[PDB]
Image 1: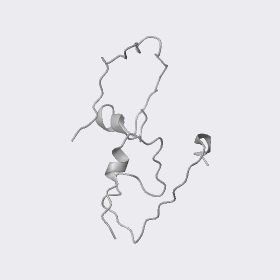
Image 2 (image 1 turned 180 degrees about the vertical axis):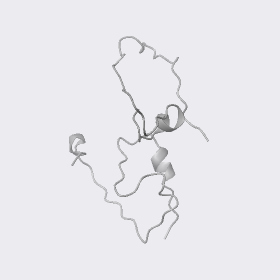
Image 3 (image 1 turned 30 degrees about the vertical axis):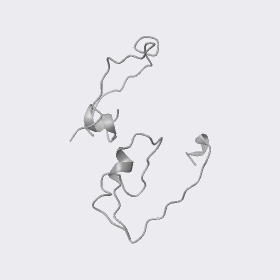
Image 4 (image 1 turned 90 degrees about the vertical axis):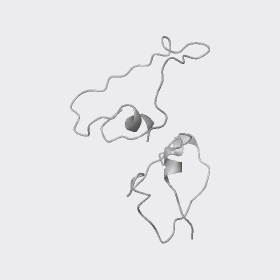
Length: 50
Length: 49
């Protein structure tokens, strides 16, 4: 129940990785969803690949 | 620096064709271009419309 803008997160250089599966990051502005869920946790750097 | 890649350089300063034929050659230059006080003579385009 909100307006999302994924260009801010995408252009930001602060992220170590930004990998999209199924989609790709510049198309996210013209697409919309019934819901989006954010799974948030801390891992070890070498575990990012997992 | 590869076909199909995006980012602030891939989009603003150096874009390759996705049908690129050729080779990408790279080596570190930490003992030549970097300087104490930093080397600020190398500029990149942070933002473009």
